[PDB]
Image 1 (cartoon, each protein chain N blue to C red):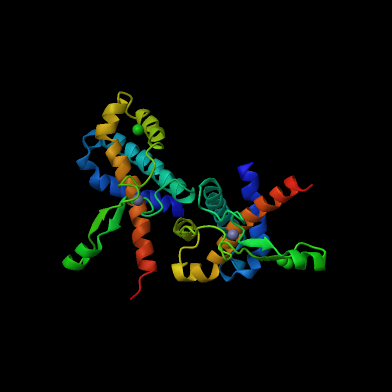
Image 2: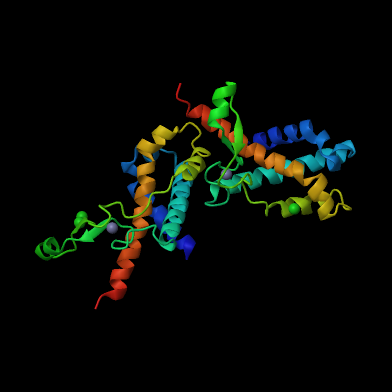
Amino acid sequence: SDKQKAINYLMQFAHKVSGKYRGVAKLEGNTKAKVLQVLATFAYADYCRSAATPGARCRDCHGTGRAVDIAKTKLWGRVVEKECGRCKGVGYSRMPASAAYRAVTMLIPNLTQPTWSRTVKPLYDALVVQCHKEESIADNILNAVT
Amino acid sequence: DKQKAINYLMQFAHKVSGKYRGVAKLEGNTKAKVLQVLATFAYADYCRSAATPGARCRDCHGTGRAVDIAKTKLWGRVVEKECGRCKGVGYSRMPASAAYRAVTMLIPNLTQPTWSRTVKPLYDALVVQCHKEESIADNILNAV
Ligand SMILES: [Cl-]
Ligand SMILES: [Cl-]
Ligand SMILES: [Cl-]
Ligand SMILES: [Zn+2]
Ligand SMILES: [Zn+2]
């Protein structure tokens, strides 16, 4: 419901950016749709578990890997980010991705893990971090002093 | 054993929830999920402090309290006073932002100031509850 809406939002984003990832960009339409749905479902679950589990994502950036660069934000008149110093940009554990790899191989049975790592997993990670970034923006808006 | 401790802390959070405006009126299902988050994160904060050298006061081991000897004798029950070494702080306070973010997934309109005034005091009470349980277990274990 609320979960399915968020998953659908994430699936639509996955389609928008899919052309950047060589392992999904040229799949047949029906397979591409199934793959992107798997990636969005696993990525959203990975995000949700990491936010609710103590220690499962970085406690300074809350998963985004990024922090505000105060001086550059002032200079440029827009939010400029830098790497999160605490997690040096990792944001969230990468171990849950193995489950997504297994689910994708059921749809792409010749996809090896190193080919996944280079050509598909970057989209999975783009989706996980997209969720942490959405949460950070929602928090910034909710708590603005203006 | 961890889940038992958290579930115990969760039940205590329910008992005292009425005293904290940010949880005392949540609807049954949401209230349970929020209190489970609070207990889970509070227990993790406690465990980190207990395991990290220097993260707790070496006299009170996190409770912020000491036994008032003269009042305990007068009243025939343990009566506490502020721990002198730490002036009642008990443990180094770490930011509770991760817990706040986990709660806001369940209560999307909860601002950080409202959290700080009306929910975070319960969170802090749950953390100290854990140090107090440890202290009682130690007292009982070492009573002659
Ligand atoms: Cl992987
Ligand atoms: Cl007392
Ligand atoms: Cl009392
Ligand atoms: Zn970080
Ligand atoms: Zn002390």
